[PDB]
Length: 166
Ligand SMILES: Nc1nc2c(ncn2[C@@H]2O[C@H](COP(=O)(O)OP(=O)(O)NP(=O)(O)O)[C@@H](O)[C@H]2O)c(=O)[nH]1
Ligand SMILES: [Ca+2]
Ligand SMILES: [Ca+2]
Ligand SMILES: [Mg+2]
Ligand SMILES: [Mg+2]
Image 1 (spheres, protein in one colour):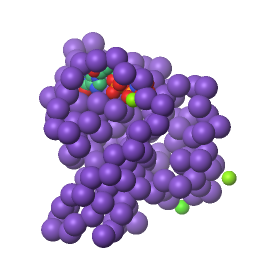
Image 2: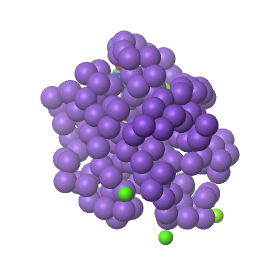
Image 3: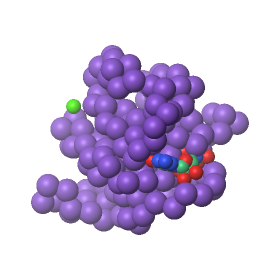
């Protein structure tokens, strides 16, 4: 079957794992569980076609930047996650976007910019700000809550469609 190599990137704690676990295991559990590097392979049907989502869930820890080159090198499309209550994580996702472009020698990489934790009240990143960044990349912006599942399928399946339409 068609395989889609999806990589979930972003600063520590923005909800990269929570998003992936909601998609694959249909649940949210509030818990502290930092990622080193985890792989989820799930066969899905998207728009009538069977495909294998090969999802790499990465670490937000700054001490892993050398290891980021490797999975950016081999990754097909990227969920670029920040949290809407964490302005620093929004600044950081600019750096991820630039690194993806440098490692892959391309500004045509399928990506979706994801503003996660949209269930939370203390918003500090406005949607228009994130939309401006996504426009500069030519990519969609989608808000998500791993907690409520709002936008989760939207974000992952839109990334698949962005790859498929590449
Ligand atoms: N309210 C709310 N909390 C969330 C959401 N997504 C994740 N969290 C919470 O935020 C924390 C970090 O989530 P996690 O998925 O582990 O983040 P991560 O980006 O994978 N971290 P790491 O880079 O260390 O692997 C956890 O307490 C988790 O329960 C969300 O959409 N809403
Ligand atoms: Ca181009
Ligand atoms: Ca597009
Ligand atoms: Mg994680
Ligand atoms: Mg280069």
